[PDB]
Image (cartoon, rainbow over all chains, first blue to last red; front, side, top):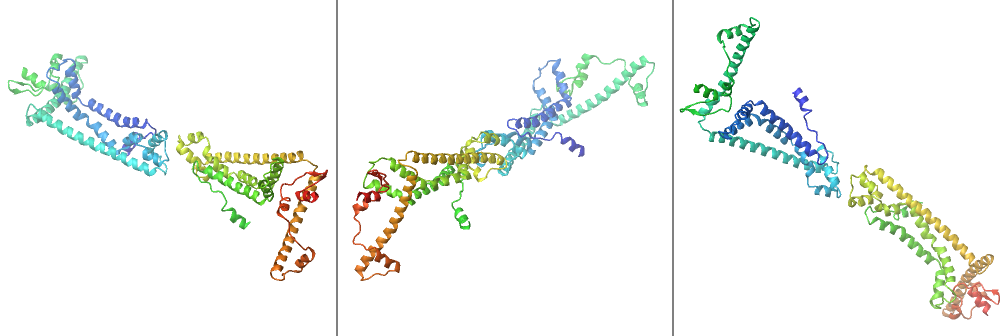
Length: 275
Length: 275
């Protein structure tokens, strides 16, 4: 609240009342926060790196661009919410759009009201309306064009949130309509991927810690463990880790080939059933 | 004073702050009072009618256009003082001239001050300066152009009163330099014309009254006189009046022919010496 206002004050809009310049600032303050939120949505997502590790060394578009497209749909479903929550919250606030298109209004009524105002004065005085710099001779006209431009901004924001709503609906019906499986089995697959990822993180931490303890014990002569780590060395000994081709056989896109009719829900499962 | 202000209020200037119109009003309020004062100066002068009676039935430009020119110089000396006292008192007041040439100023500084003001707005806002209708953005500019135009008006008024001063000086040196006589004899001639005109008016009233009394006495049987008129009938009887060619021999321009060297100062004197 307090720190939220103290951070929202610097990011707040300040319309530069200048023609052919304010619309560039409006485009920046709309798009560039939406762009950085979009790119950190791709950054925060981990399955993007699964995709790039799938296509870099394998160089395999052999299946199709459609499993990559469904993966990318999950990517943008995690990611692209952040640009579109910013674009609509700017558009319905309308400040960026009035600062954008204040210098594009038909000045005919303004020229009739301002005793034949010339386009050199008209475009510049149109740009000065979002700073409320209109005089008393044009304050009502500035309020009228400000309300019409606020209308256009809010209508564009509502149309954009409507079309992204129908877009997310259509990609859900596409994902369930181009599905190679049920929706109960897709839920089982989602729970399998969550269980495998959580179990794999926990066992990677445990196996890495046991390997580190064996190396340290080889160095010093002993190790410094809590009782939990003493139980870890007691329970799960290691002779050696896993080779890098065997590690490469695990990563990649989540396949759904079915070995001998029985399904394989991930590449680790494919690798385990392959042995 | 009080009635003078009550009459000066209606004749006072009211500048119509409108372009290509206010200068016509300034030209009217300068010239037309000067024109009517000039024409009533010709009307009030009686020697104009002496000139037109000299040139109408005689149709005689036989002497020259120069005695007519000296007579007309006396005409305008009596007359033309009234237009030129009006033109300078309007010009030094400056209101007619600022109302005239407010719509002719170079609007370049006004266009630079008024954010590229167009000539459609500039000429009309130039015309509105003599009503002090400039805003705060141009009040100082209106004061500057008003003072410069007041300068131009007062300088033109001073130059006009200077040139009419040198003009009246040059026509006096012309009249004394193209004089056919002395200046003492010209003073004697002026006193002769005044004495002849006054004596002729008095004896015309007296002789007309005695003729009217003789006609009335022929009608009723008597007359109604005061004691002064009784003395008038007692002193100056009339048999008959004077014929119209003899009356035409009196009127005309004041000649200065000299019969046998001895001068004749007016046409009555010429007529008397001719008998």
